[PDB]
Image (cartoon, coloured by chain):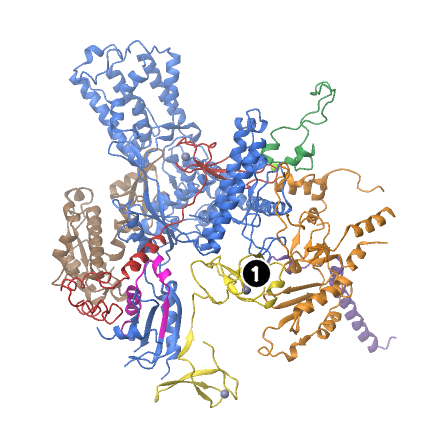
Chain colours: A blue, B orange, C green, D red, E yellow, F purple, G brown
Amino acid sequence: DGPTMREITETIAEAKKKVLDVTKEAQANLLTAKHGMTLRESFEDNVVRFLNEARDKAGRLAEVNLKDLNNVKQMVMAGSKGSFINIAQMSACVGQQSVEGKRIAFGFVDRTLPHFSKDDYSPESKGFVENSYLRGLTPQEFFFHAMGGREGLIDTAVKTAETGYIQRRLVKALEDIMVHYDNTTRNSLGNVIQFIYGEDGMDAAHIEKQSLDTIGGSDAAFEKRYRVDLLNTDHTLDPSLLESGSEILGDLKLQVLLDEEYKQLVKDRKFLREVFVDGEANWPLPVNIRRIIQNAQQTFHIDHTKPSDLTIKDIVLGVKDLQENLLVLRGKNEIIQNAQRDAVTLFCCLLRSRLATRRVLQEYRLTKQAFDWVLSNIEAQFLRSVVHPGEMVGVLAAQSIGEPATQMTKKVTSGVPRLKEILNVAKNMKTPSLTVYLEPGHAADQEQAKLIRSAIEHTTLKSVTIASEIYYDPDPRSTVIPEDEEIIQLHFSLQQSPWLLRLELDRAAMNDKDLTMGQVGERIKQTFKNDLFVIWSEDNDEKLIIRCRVVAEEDHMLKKIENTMLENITLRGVENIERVVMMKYDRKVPSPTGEYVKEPEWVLETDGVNLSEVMTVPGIDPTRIYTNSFIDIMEVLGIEAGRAALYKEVYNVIASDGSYVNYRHMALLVDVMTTQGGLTSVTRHGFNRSNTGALM
Amino acid sequence: SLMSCISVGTDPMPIITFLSEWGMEPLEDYVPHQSPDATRVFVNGVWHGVHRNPARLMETLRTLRRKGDINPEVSMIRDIREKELKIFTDAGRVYRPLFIVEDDESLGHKELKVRKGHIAKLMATEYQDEYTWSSLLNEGLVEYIDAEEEESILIAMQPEDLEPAEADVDPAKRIRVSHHATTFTHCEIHPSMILGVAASIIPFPDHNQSPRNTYQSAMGKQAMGVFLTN
Amino acid sequence: ASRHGQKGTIGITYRREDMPFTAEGIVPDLIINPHAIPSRMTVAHLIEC
Amino acid sequence: AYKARYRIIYSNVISKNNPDLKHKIANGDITPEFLATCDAKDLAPAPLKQKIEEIAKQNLYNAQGATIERSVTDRFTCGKCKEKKVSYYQLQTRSADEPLTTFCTCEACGNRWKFS
Amino acid sequence: TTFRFCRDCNNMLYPREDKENNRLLFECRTCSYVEEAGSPLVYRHELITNIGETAGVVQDIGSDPTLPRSDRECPKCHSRENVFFQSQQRRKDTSMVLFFVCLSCSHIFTSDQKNKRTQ
Amino acid sequence: KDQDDRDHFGKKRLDLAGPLLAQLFKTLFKKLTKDIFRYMQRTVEEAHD
Amino acid sequence: DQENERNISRLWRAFRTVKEMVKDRGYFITQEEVELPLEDFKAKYCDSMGRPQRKMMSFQANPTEESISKFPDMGSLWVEFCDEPSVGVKTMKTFVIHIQEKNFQTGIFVYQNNITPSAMKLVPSIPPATIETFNEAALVVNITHHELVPKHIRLSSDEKRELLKRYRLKESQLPRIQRADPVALYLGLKRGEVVKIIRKSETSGRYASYRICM
Ligand SMILES: [Mg+2]
Ligand SMILES: [Zn+2]
Ligand SMILES: [Zn+2]
Ligand SMILES: [Zn+2]
């Protein structure tokens, strides 16, 4: 539209000013950097953010103005081709161009092109393509889009071989893995990788995302859905629900059975809440029970009026019995029988939730034959659902991770290069980071977060110092620097070197990394003990100074002392831990009323790793603390945790690209790297150096 | 790109001989603290000496090139901030020709040396098939600028659109910037010349997504047609 | 291919009678799919035309 | 121791314171015683209290971790938290013949995915 | 700092303490030369530097076409004719403060609305 | 000052047909020069004209 | 007061974890014994200055009724702490013979900073009895309590024999826990000993894996 184009132009126009406004603000030194960022880094972030907010607004304007008759909108609507951005870029505005994440940089001295003035941080100078493809690009817009365009072609080109080799290594490490006739996953050595395929003994094709009802809702809402009380006139099953309704009231013997039923359902709820901590209900499980019920309903032409011919015993026991027939493992012995129970656990919680008495009668309105049929079908389906001995689950898993890696395009190393880091069990990783969760109580307390941030983020005498100076001040009692005259007059009233080491500290720096002259001085004093005489200017006093003296030949001696001071003296924090950011992560937690509710917390984000040390810090949750470096998790928390971290990490790489790979595949890889007792890499060094066959 | 050429490589001596004669103190007699603001002069990464008033020297050297006395393929750059004057007689440097703009105009502002009279003077020679490209080059209307020299210049994209200041607007046309600069040393002959042989057959490449253009400049190489009449 | 990185092979060849036609009696030499254009954002192809 | 215481214271016174111382015285013783214791110183120381107390604040500040701020488009939807508050960023995953992958992120529930 | 050399050698000077009269000297380690110190300051480190900001400000600064202009009235001659640039100290941290150089009086003024300068 | 941009085009040269032949001709002419010398020894020993 | 109280908190936090490990290993320790408050720790093992008296801390522990049912030959344990940050051959020879005379089966030595290589050479000197060295600093936090650390359960000679029988295995074919593994240390697993890991599954709810010691 003509007015939509005016409205778009005026959207860019206002964003263009918003940017100039932040630029004028930055040139006037009024800009205040975000903790753990350059004043400049902070600025560029804002500029980039406004310009994108703009491209999208301008886009969403056109997208709305295009009628349903728009052939492009029509393709986007069906999902046949194209997305929002395509409309936006074509109709309204192309947007900001990036190379290496940052805007077009100054290839020429202080400018992007020779058509610009130096020190031009304007959108037009750093690659913002204001125009739509329909309108056309200016030569500058054209070349910047060309730079940005070339970047993608480079990774498309490279990724292609990197991605290829990743695939090979996964395949060669897993090839010999398959399910044997004992449901055990073993390699060419008969070494057990997984005891049962993908911890459930099921084939992945036969699985579907299903909702575990029991898991969520209020404790009251659960009760209404599941509780049958034949000893209470209000909470009995109405005689409209089943034929025996009238004769069922007050049956103490029967009530014993509904008590077991409800007690199990409550047991299950707690258990599932232990497994899925967030309260996520939707999980991939075999047998779509929802569909079986739906079918029973049309198959049997279920009359949602007349009462059922079911007994409470018919339902209660029927389910109890079906459960014993859901066979994954067959052996006649405690080990194998307990194993069978284990594999079937989760599926049963679902089964018991969907087939509880109240549910079957009130909701499903099933007849005895309908129910009898539903039961047989769950059984049949479940059995068909188990993995087939012979399944080459090894290659499957490798290819199931390999193929998605092939489609791959706080700021942490992710995607293809991270997967590379992971598989290689890379010692010197690119983005090491700790995720420090706070102590239970003080979870919402921002001031507590700051306290730990301060107690953990590394601080050196160097980070606070403006400059150090060596002076010849021969009288320890009287000073050649008239400034210092007052500092002596006090730090004397209420033998040593004539050579003075005088350092000036930055008040602004001494504040962001909260510190006192007293505490800084104390560290130096406590470092050099009784072989260095330290004095310091007060936190109040205008200039921030620390005067130091030792206890023939002394010039070089003091130059060593100043290097020790700047480089080796640690003030606050833990070693290896730099840039600590405070973060308000959202956490799903059960409320007193039962329902899972958003209760966000303050979380710390590290720029480095030291597990052993940060764990022992007061004020954190040492039960919750996580690092992306699984090599550390392994070393500190054992091989079991090493496995859990290694999976978490692998899973993230896939899900970050917005892809889904079934658990089992990632689980298997993770397990194979694990089994040996450590971190066996998917490299010529790791797997290929095991006890397998020589030709292999 | 279409207008790109590569420096054949000339002789440095006529320039070294010229320099010494134009106020260049030889390095052999340099005394850093005596002349401390001295602009250091290089010819092919060889420091030959220093000069006290580079402003005037630079103008003489530029007039030498724009006349033809100093070859047009020779690159000479003056980084004022760094106090350096580097000269390249050197072979292998990629250069492009640009229109020269001069503050020099009795009547008004800073204006492109080339005038509508030269343009008709060329199209007269276009009808003949006496005024060549060399004719524009020796009349110092146009110049050769390599990447190192590009660093110190300031180019206008369009001449007419980027010259006289402001003393309604079509909505269908693309959003364009301005001629805010009063400093303009050069002007772009035509911005489409940034493109190579293959990309120059792409119709409206300013209306395509960046790689779709990169694709065509690869496919057209595999397109059938008459390759030669023989 | 067109001059817009819009490449492809022939899927079928139809005679003039099978082809869709303008009231004016004009028929296409080539039928290209709408699905090319959006994801690709080759606007100049449409303008060329 | 004582011584120381015483011384120282014483010383212181011285210183210055013175015055115171013176016263012482016166015173018572117581114162011382116381111283021783414381221591015383603050108381013791013053009058520093203000500054010393104010200086802590700048340090709180320097302790918080950058907030990735991002837009949400009202024509883009999540697969769980079924809400129209999602962010996206496109990259060139495939060769120059298919163009623009476009990755999504439910800025509220946290799922991510591709469009091709 | 600003250090001296030995007249006679031209070789650099090393500091020596005159233990008796409690005073600093500068000795030459190539000849027998000695001279008393000008300042008590022998070594200055300087971590948070400001020397580099206004570098290469040749009076010819106006002759750079690459430099941008502004209509900001000068603190001295009040001239609305000046070229501008950012802190030439090529560090990451560095603020986006601007330095304006007068196309008449040559005085260097800044845009800093937090602090007041003289360089 | 900033670290030198190893990718600045101004700091790159293009060796065309000229210099390529010059590089080859040098090593090819010194190959001939030192084969004539090997001959001048062979022909001064026996005075073989 | 200063930063003295914090080394106390840490020694107490360490002590709780020692008590936790000991009960876990299969020894008789109460919950109130573990859950001992900080104030109560101070007013027990602190001198006439509130300085930790680690010599007092050292304690003996006996197998639970339940433990002798699974492992009969499971004898008594001795846990010794030390007030000397660096422990040498002098303090070690004292503790070493102490275990041999009191006919102890196992002995843990919780050290502050180090144990000299002189003293470390006396560790495997008195068999069938066994000696363990634990750096106080590791124990401040019980790793077993972590989100990612699942239930490991040590199997008996009969339980192991059965595992291998039930799965038709050679010890080669079992996944392996490394001897030095944080949890293998916490449980004082010996080479050949097997653990049963019970982890939660997004797949099955509960999954049992086994690991043999290195
Ligand atoms: Mg292809
Ligand atoms: Zn969402
Ligand atoms: Zn001398
Ligand atoms: Zn002025």
- State ligand 1's quadrant: top right
- Disc 1 element: strand
Using the image as rendered, state which of residue C25 and residue G207 is in the foreground.
C25
Using the image as rendered, state which of residue G15 and residue D107 is in the foreground.
D107
> Which residue occupies 53% across, 31% down?
A63
Q: Is residue A444 magenta?
A: no
Name the spot of residue A227 as percent of width and height, x first.
Answer: 23, 22
Q: Residues within 10 Å of mark 1 (few under 14, many from 20)?
A: many
Quadrant (top left, top right, bottom left, bottom right) of the N terminus of chain A: top right
Start and end of the magenta stretch? Answer: A501-530
Name the spot of residue A260 as percent of width and height, x first.
Answer: 21, 24
Using the image as rendered, state which of residue A584 and residue A175 is in the foreground.
A584
Q: Which residue is mark 1?
A: E82
From the viewer's perspective, tell me whether residue A480 is left or right of residue G6: right
Regarding residue G134, the answer to whether it shows in the image is no
Position of residue G70 relative to residue F45, above or below, is above
Q: Is mark 1 within 8 Å of ligand 4?
A: yes
Amino acid carrying mark 1 in the image: Asn
> Which residue occupies 24% across, 13% down?
A238
Q: Is residue A514 magenta?
A: yes
Regarding residue A546, the answer to whether it shows in the image is yes
